[PDB]
Image (tube, rainbow over all chains, first blue to last red; front, side, top):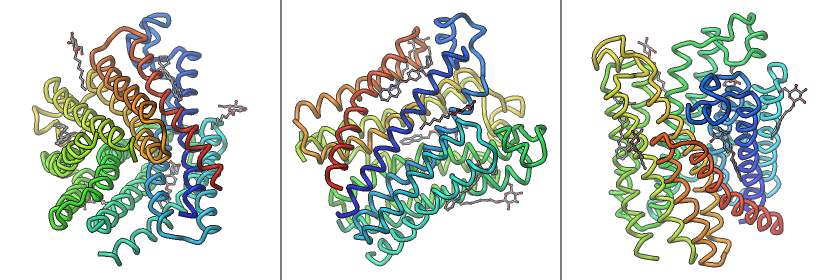
Length: 143
Length: 143
Length: 143
Ligand SMILES: O=C(O)[C@@H](c1ccc(OCc2ccc3ccccc3n2)cc1)C1CCCC1
Ligand SMILES: O=C(O)[C@@H](c1ccc(OCc2ccc3ccccc3n2)cc1)C1CCCC1
Ligand SMILES: O=C(O)[C@@H](c1ccc(OCc2ccc3ccccc3n2)cc1)C1CCCC1
Ligand SMILES: CCCCCCCCO[C@@H]1O[C@H](CO)[C@@H](O)[C@H](O)[C@H]1O
Ligand SMILES: CCCCCCCCO[C@@H]1O[C@H](CO)[C@@H](O)[C@H](O)[C@H]1O
Ligand SMILES: CCCCCCCCO[C@@H]1O[C@H](CO)[C@@H](O)[C@H](O)[C@H]1O
């Protein structure tokens, strides 16, 4: 598929981007001394450190939003790649998603003013919606 | 694959169904004035609106359950499609999952009496379990 | 693909492992009488049972970590299988992930001392990182 290399590049970068969030989460837990498990807290200073922290919670929300958005893209974009779309159009779909999602993480973890984060979220969803509809038509017509 | 069009139809509809939940979540946050981020709250009335809401939490639980169930289906159903199953049997697997999952969201967000939601959850898991076992046998025998 | 049977075996076992966590979660909710929904609580003893429980929360954290790690593997490992890697090397990637993830669930739900869980988490991520980089190179060179 001509679109597949671009899809695999963008998707893998987004998986790596999620791994970055996972690592940041751990770093914040250690720095802020905020653990979700007693066994963790007892290792890292005592039971008083089994507690919630706003920065940790923020990291978790960013990671969750990633899972809600990037995982569908992994599916939709893979299938879309094999439908034989216009190369440039396909690239635009993938680039809008990649840029939008990277911007989303920056806006979330960087605590940027509203509605920057929400805009990046919505924007990145648009190529996903587009791919979804295209797959729907292709699937339905092949029934 | 003869089963693949039906799989792609059901899967894409389920992705769209998850997007519907994502949009509803936002609508409920705005209507109930309940935001998870201070930057959101300050935009939408003040810091007192950085708060939890039962309806918002319900939306999040529905979306989470979707991610726990639909994402495995996206994987299992794709692989299963290429194993050359009986067309009608394959359709039944996909339809049970689709109907069960749509019913699940309705039961969750509609606050239907127990155990309606839990039944739909369990029911929809059954075709997934079936596909999983079939893939296990095929994979193992090809080792 | 020569690596594909091993990938499909390990992946399906991990999906089943996640289903086990889902079932355990339900069992713990019923045993500890801790429900997230009023409709559930009213069915199972009264409104006082709409409450949080540490064991339930632990189950949810284990399931969430699974979704953060196993879902990327489902994607990365599938693509990696088609890149024509060394059979034994591919097997090692998949086995390290499988063993690491099973150990992770045991360490989490079994409340094993730190840093056993965190080590298993980190260890299992290493083959994923490896596959991600390999896909990046292949994708980039095919642009
Ligand atoms: O939740 C936990 O178990 C801990 C924890 C432990 C390890 C973490 O990143 C590993 C990781 C994540 C992603 C990777 C991607 C590629 C390669 C290695 C990777 N490695 C994060 C949190 C925290 C709580 C106690 C101490 C920190
Ligand atoms: O969490 C947030 O960032 C906000 C928010 C912002 C946007 C939302 O839906 C976008 C969306 C979702 C799914 C889509 C699927 C297809 C096409 C467009 C799509 N667009 C939801 C919540 C809420 C908090 C502050 C205001 C609401
Ligand atoms: O959250 C809920 O809806 C309930 C609930 C209900 C059912 C559950 O496992 C089903 C399941 C899960 C995974 C499967 C995998 C294969 C085959 C059947 C499978 N079946 C768990 C929790 C709990 C709250 C009220 C009572 C328990
Ligand atoms: C893909 C991973 C991107 C990580 C984005 C990290 C954004 C760091 O941005 C930082 O955010 C802080 C608030 O959290 C601010 O105090 C700093 O001014 C800002 O530099
Ligand atoms: C795929 C998306 C399906 C959305 C299902 C929304 C269900 C709306 O159902 C509504 O639920 C309310 C309680 O929340 C009740 O007050 C109403 O009687 C009922 O109509
Ligand atoms: C793939 C699913 C694996 C489930 C792992 C369950 C681990 C059970 O392990 C149990 O944990 C208890 C604490 O929770 C301890 O009291 C027990 O000593 C221990 O046997």
